[PDB]
Image (cartoon, rainbow, N blue to C red; front, side, top):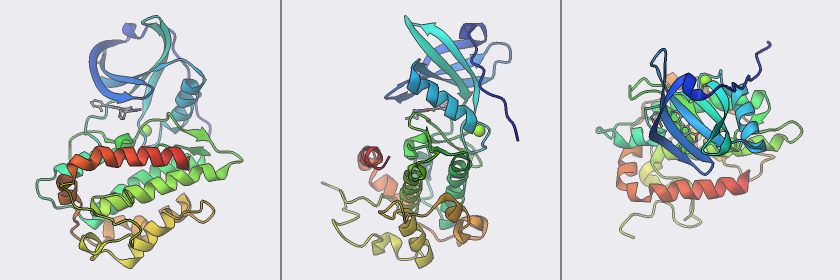
Length: 290
Ligand SMILES: CN1CC2(CNC(=O)c3c2[nH]c2c3CCc3cnc(-c4ccccc4F)cc3-2)C1
Ligand SMILES: [Mg+2]
């Protein structure tokens, strides 16, 4: 099938949208502000990039990805002058449900189940699949870039941030780090801490120890552990691919996976002072796996 290419608008964005000062996110590449379409009054998000080759690649690759139901949608892209600099202003659908793990952490029940984790991974998996099959690797799949459409329990999860995406034609192992990200996310979903070796807090993984500590992992099947191990495999030549992953019975039959109660929500609350550290370890790790 054939799709339309990206048409960058040159008219001033203020002809079309009201632009507020409320920041809805921060990025080592620019900011995200709140805005409203003038004629319809619909709310939208605005990502601002200083125009450059990298910004252009971000917008292009994200444009290709945009129609995926589990990737955030680009409504329009503008090339404008702002504050004395030439910018790409990107209008996206509003995603005000919060980040993936904040939600889980906030569950007053502390009632999160293996099945729920499966369905979430199928969602993320679908984004990665859409991308990998058009030879794009995202390369920044991590907690802060996964957001929900609304606060509704039934909100859709969306992958954001194409700042590190690249075309992978002829360098297939670029896709691998997206798979490791899936492994890491799945592991945190299942227990509340990442599979990282790393005062007034429990140590969840001892340095060098077996990866699935009994307190939190005792009721998780060996099949699931094997799935994680395949995703986390050290060697990119041996790591699971997105096709193998989306063909796995635990993902393919997500809705019929056991509702094993998990420690995830309680651990996220217990360890909340360490979350920034978690995100920072993952970011540093990503920089070396890309
Ligand atoms: C670290 N966070 C993720 C962050 C960085 N890079 C992005 O592309 C990015 C980021 N946040 C967003 C986006 C684009 C889609 C997007 C859409 N909507 C929101 C958003 C809208 C209303 C209220 C709160 C929100 F987070 C926020 C984002 C800021
Ligand atoms: Mg989409």
